[PDB]
Image (cartoon, rainbow, N blue to C red):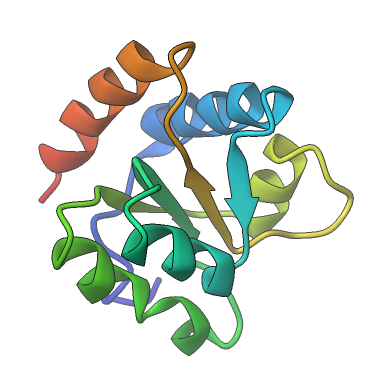
Length: 120
């Protein structure tokens, strides 16, 4: 695992994050792709950015950490782009998911963000 892929969530937190993604997906509240995530972050529409550590080339997702920190947006790496794809409800691997604001997600995102930041 690339050392730049931090903070890196463990297996239980990863599953929490994936279930949050799935929930967001049902509400049309996530964007996929490193490009789309960067655009949401810069426009202040991102509450959380999730990044697959096995993205290839990994450089495609390595602009997000600094862009997120500049804006106080929480971000975290998980292990599997295949898992992330399934959670986004698509058939293809996904290397980045950004979660937008939604009343139905407010509190779980904040709880999870508390755990992500404990990793920093």
